[PDB]
Image (cartoon, rainbow, N blue to C red; front, side):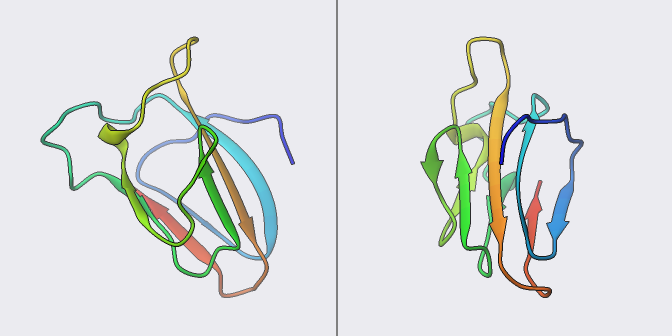
Length: 86
């Protein structure tokens, strides 16, 4: 998969299939532990070329791209597979 679209927060994705998406609404603040990605059923989740599928990661933890936004990648294998971003 490839060629990202913009998304809006809070975000959620479901159902067997493979994707990219982008955003710039991600908080940068060192206080913002309550804003995160987390996954359990997904075969893959990467953000700017680091894998997090079996864990959680906060938006404030990740540096932006040079053009000023974050890249997110997802893969699902199942009809019950879902994910959530704050």
